[PDB]
């Protein structure tokens, strides 16, 4: 639309909230592929932060490419490597969700503030494979990664 | 619909067509390989069947225990393969149980199990999955025969239903009788065969069971890959027709939207 | 007019919901299996 | 021109069989080779930011890429090869780069020198 | 005359051929089939098959298991499970396998395990004897 | 009655063991091809 | 369009005739899902009439949902309940077609009137599955359902 | 608030795995989703008091209806109310006045639903 | 679009240069099948010209259809009355290419201005099968058919 289209050029950072992601229950529904920042360069944030971010974006885009195939084959017929991409992508998709201190009324959960180093560590670990045994739902609406581990432990105990 | 609805639908169908073309090519390659492998297996299995059609064996008419094995696969998108197999399997099971028998069922491949899990859900002696991912070998047939013999349902008669591969476009559903040594021993024809105790004959029956399972597996995989190739070709053709229709609709809608916006601008300009 | 990746689930037609369900059922099953293994590891590592 | 004609031809071949990339296996050897070469070439065309390259550097890199000297390297490593390799030639072999630059073409002697350089560097990379 | 048919699951050697003699090793002691052998149906044993072509030419294939059916009309169906020509085999490897199998023999967790192990010894002994 | 039949086995297992014993003693190059066209991949689901 | 869209709010019963259906040969081409009415209320038409109408609409809507997949993947990638739904829905679609007397000249058929009880009974029977052994083209353009059965018998010959 | 929250979660999970129709867990998830869906239906010009809605939704979401067929759920619904509306007016008055499912109210509701389900 | 929708009302023919044919080295890269003409009518261009053109179009379409089979089932799957059509269609494709007088600095040959009778006779002979024994490359980038004969002699001897 002309109004948002024109507004795009006046901003340094943008966070394009998406309805297709809010339907899935991932909140905040920030679209990871339609959001950008000016400082998002390796010389401003650091090479670790930049590489983690680009790895996350690439894995999500590969997931989108695979979703077209899964609509005809099915998850059961994917290359045992592609299933790994899908699993990592879903874990990363859920791990971006977070509970706010102002959305207590809706979710009922409790707000979490995640320091930057903890987010970078969490996503770097999720990509590196250090969690490819925990189920997806363990990562849904939690702060740092250790909270996902604890939630998975609780899920297993009350299994 | 509106222009964005049409655009999204058109993009989705284009992706679907691309995927179905790629799947056709993959299925064609696998079909070529499976046919190449089927020739030697064809001769081998026909030779293994040789005896029962050389020394005609009539199954006993005083026994009730029967086995139905149905070879298919786990993969879908192969047209009327699993459907035909399961249809004939339930036909045979109904005929046997109406004539008064105690039928069981072995399903080589999920899709047979699924088609028959509503009715005949309790006759499953045992079912095998993980079929179709890689071409079947003699290891698979040996495993199936071993888990059939071990599962102590000593049957009195058997049948195997598979899709015999006729031509690249056509296949037929067969029923190949499987006999137990209780029938082979009690056959006048077998009186001639020399050095035929009831132990060498038992080993021979086990081996022939493995042989027939392997033959059915090779024929079934060949026909399944051919059917998947044909199904993907038809699906891609249908997606192409739908893409043509939707492209025509999209062009109409795009022109209509341009004209509508322009008329709005003109009316506003002239209405000052 | 072109096509782009991840469009089947952008339309949200029938193939989109079919794909969503085909994914969700499979990963529910795998989550169940992994949770069972996690419980087993918990018990076996208590000592 | 010499290197880009082949690069463009190979990329065009790769773009019409890119759909199979997810499948890839269970296809003939020709399409396997097309996919492999295309992936290597695309990983070659990747570039940093605010890091332009002189023409001699570009031609050296693309020449290494399009003659098969990267068909053994794994794609994830190409973006590293391209890097390290480049530094090598930009430090050890300045005479060849200057020859290519000023001359404007790849003379047979320069072609042989590029062959030897690429093989020697690739012969020990890891 | 014979209608020989020697076919592994993967590859097929003779199809409806017309050979002279076939020396085959079965469970009930090896033997040989000629033009009008009495009908039989035996189960092979880890040995080797010697086929004398319609003349005096002889070829040896090592068979691991299978079944040999000799029918009334002089048709022999000799279906192996892994028939490999001798030239494809290795010698010392057979001895190493035989010795390792014998070593594991004493570790007989139960009777059936020992039966399995010294079936392996049986096959390796047949291999070395064929190559020795 | 072979010894292994006195153990309650079946000739299919005997053939499996003999096949392993014969396919493990091939020229090193032939083993790569022999891995194909052999070795099951089937699973059994308890009913 | 503004004109029909505005007229819709001035009507008790509608009857959206459709060209897509008319191209299938169905006649009258009434679209069963766009057509509506104010008196389609269990307190006015009954409970058998209302239940039958809602069952027909539900099965037709399920068939419409399947149509997109059926058109590409083919009618083979369908569960058995879905194949039953497709068959029932096609039988119902054909059965809603009727031969008018004013069209006696067009087609040479004979005009048919179908009292309400016969309509409700025929659709009850089709819905219950009483006629799953007939061919779907046995319902194309007939009066009451017994005429469909007679047509199927003639088809057998 | 107590009951509709669990119902909302159950329908949210059901909608994800609904487009098709195996294992016990997801099969029961679909069963519960369908039971709740047929529970939410309603007629015209017959709004229900909030406590009656709570009773019906509680019966549906506490896995009681999972035994029944889905095509019959509506029956239960209607019948259940016509029972509770006469014999157990006191419980509904309690729920309305106190405005919550207290522990004793929950135990009652439990026994009423358990008794009614078998007797029907 | 109104622009081409309005211009196409006036066109009396059509030529379709295709990138997919300049790849094959055929020149002029005119798409033989997508090209159209209004006067391709036996009443205008004559029965012999019309029949030759229709035969060439049919054989080219047949080869196009067969190319899918070649790509999938492999060249072996063809009959003997189809391998022959493949050979004839490849020869026709080669013969449709020509060397231009204004492109002697691109092809190394000398441009030919083939009259009409020469073209019709050449394609009539190729369709009849009179040249099935020659190599395909003997037809590439030559003028009349006699030049194809001479090229075959010069490259085979």
Image (tube, coloured by chain):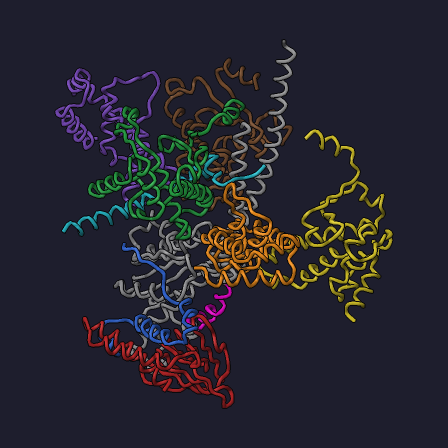
Chain colours: A green, C cyan, D orange, E red, F blue, G brown, H purple, I yellow
Residue occupying the far left of the picture:
H104
Please give the range of residues in magenta.
Answer: B35-48
- Which quarter of the rendered picture does the N terminus of chain I lie within? top right
Which of the two residues, B92 or I102, is positioned nearer the viewer here?
I102
Nearer the observer, G119 or I12 = I12
- Tell me the quadrant of the picture where the C terminus of chain I can be found: bottom right
Residue I122 point in image, percent of width and height? 82, 57
Residue visible at 35% across and 44% down in the picture = A124
| Residue H71 in view, yes or no | no
Number of on-image labels: 0
- Quadrant hosting residue F38: bottom left
* Left or right, residue B33 beside residue I33: left
Vertical order, A6 against F33 (above or below)? above
Task: Give the percent coordinates (x, y) of residue I64.
Answer: 66, 53
Give the x, y percent position of residue H88: 16, 20
Instruction: Between residue G45 and residue D72, name the one nearer to us.
Output: D72
Is the magenta region chiefly helix, strand or loop?
A: helix
Residue for point 50% across, 56% down = D88
Q: Residue at x 45, y 54 (%)?
A: D77
Residue B37 part of the magenta-drawn span: yes
Which residue is more in the foreground, E38 or A72?
A72
Which residue reaches farthest top? B272
**Residue E100 percent coordinates (x, y):** 27, 77
Residue A70 belongs to magenta span: no
């Amino acid at each position: 639309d002309p109004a948002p289209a024109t507004t795009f050029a006046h901003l340094d950072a943008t966070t394009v909230l998406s309805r297709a992601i809010a339907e899935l229950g991932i909140y905040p529904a920030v679209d990871p592929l339609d959001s950008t920042s000016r400082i998002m360069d390796p010389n401003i944030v650091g090479s670790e932060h930049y590489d983690v971010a680009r790895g996350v974006q690439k894995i999500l885009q590969d997931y989108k490419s695979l979703q077209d195939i899964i609509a005809i084959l099915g998850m059961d017929e994917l290359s045992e490597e592609d299933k790994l991409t899908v699993s990592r992508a879903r874990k990363i998709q859920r791990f971006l969700s977070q509970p706010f201190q102002v959305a207590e009324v809706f979710t009922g959960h409790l707000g979490k503030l995640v320091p930057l180093k903890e987010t970078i560590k969490g996503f770097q670990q999720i990509l590196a494979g250090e969690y490819d045994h925990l189920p997806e739902q363990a990562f849904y609406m939690v702060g740092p990664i250790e909270e996902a581990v604890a939630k998975a432990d609780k899920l297993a105990e009350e299994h | 619909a509106t222009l964005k609805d049409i655009t999204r639908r058109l993009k989705s169908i284009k992706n679907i067509q691309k995927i179905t073309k790629s799947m056709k090519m993959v299925a064609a390659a696998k079909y070529a390989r499976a046919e190449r492998e089927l020739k030697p297996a064809r001769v081998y299995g026909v030779g293994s069947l040789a005896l029962y059609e050389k020394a005609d064996i009539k199954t006993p008419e005083d026994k009730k225990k029967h086995l139905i094995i149905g070879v298919s696969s786990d993969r879908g998108l192969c047209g009327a393969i699993h459907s035909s197999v399961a249809k004939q399997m339930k036909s045979e099971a109904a005929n046997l149980a109406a004539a008064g028998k105690e039928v069981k069922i072995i399903g080589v491949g999920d899709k047979i199990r699924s088609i028959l899990h509503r009715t005949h859900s309790d006759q499953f002696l045992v079912t095998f999955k993980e079929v179709g991912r890689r071409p079947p070998t003699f290891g698979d047939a040996s495993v199936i025969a071993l888990e059939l013999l071990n599962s102590g349902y000593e049957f009195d008669e058997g049948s195997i239903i598979f899709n015999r591969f006729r031509s690249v476009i056509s296949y037929k559903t067969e029923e190949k009788p499987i006999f137990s040594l209780d029938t082979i021993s009690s056959a006048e024809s077998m009186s001639i065969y020399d050095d035929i105790d009831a132990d060498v004959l038992r080993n021979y029956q086990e081996y022939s069971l493995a042989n027939i399972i392997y033959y059915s597996l090779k024929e079934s995989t060949t026909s399944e890959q051919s059917a998947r190739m044909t199904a993907m070709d038809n699906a891609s053709k249908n997606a192409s027709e739908m893409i043509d229709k939707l492209t025509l609709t999209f062009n109409r809608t795009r022109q209509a939207v341009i004209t509508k916006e322009l008329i709005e601008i003109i009316s506003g300009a002239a209405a000052l | 007019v072109r096509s782009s990746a991840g469009a089947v689930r952008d339309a949200g037609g029938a193939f989109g919901k079919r794909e969503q369900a085909e994914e969700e059922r499979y990963f529910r099953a795998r989550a169940k299996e992994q949770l069972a293994a996690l419980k087993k590891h918990h018990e076996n590592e208590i000592s | 021109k010499q290197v880009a004609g082949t690069m463009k031809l190979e990329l065009a071949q790769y773009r019409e069989v890119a759909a199979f990339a997810q499948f890839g296996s269970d296809l003939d050897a020709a399409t396997q080779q097309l996919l492999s070469r295309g992936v290597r070439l695309t990983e070659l065309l990747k570039q940093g930011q605010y890091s332009p390259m002189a023409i001699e550097e570009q031609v050296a890199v693309i020449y290494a890429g399009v003659r098969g000297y990267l068909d053994k390297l794994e794609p994830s490593k190409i973006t590293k090869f391209e890097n390290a390799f480049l530094s090598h030639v930009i430090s050890q072999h300045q005479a060849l780069l200057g020859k290519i630059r000023t001359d404007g073409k790849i003379s047979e002697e320069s072609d042989a020198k590029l062959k030897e350089i690429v093989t020697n560097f690739l012969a020990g990379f890891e | 005359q014979m209608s020989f048919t020697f076919a592994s699951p993967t590859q097929v050697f003779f199809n409806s051929a017309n050979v002279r003699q076939v020396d085959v090793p079965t469970q009930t002691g090896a033997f040989g089939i000629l033009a009008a052998h009495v009908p039989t149906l035996q189960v092979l044993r880890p040995g080797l098959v010697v086929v004398h072509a319609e003349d005096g030419t002889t070829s040896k294939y090592f068979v691991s298991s299978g079944s040999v059916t000799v029918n009334a009309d002089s048709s022999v169906q000799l279906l192996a499970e892994e028939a490999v020509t001798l030239d494809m085999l290795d010698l010392g490897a057979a001895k190493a396998n035989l010795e390792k199998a014998q070593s594991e023999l004493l570790g007989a967790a139960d009777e059936a395990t020992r039966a399995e192990i010294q079936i392996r010894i049986e096959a390796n002994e047949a291999l070395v004897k064929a190559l020795e | 009655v072979a010894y292994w039949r006195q153990a309650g086995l079946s000739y299919i297992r005997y053939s499996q063991i003999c096949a392993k014993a014969v396919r493990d003693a091939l020229k090193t190059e032939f083993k790569a091809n022999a891995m194909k066209t052999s070795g099951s991949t089937i699973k059994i689901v308890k009913v």
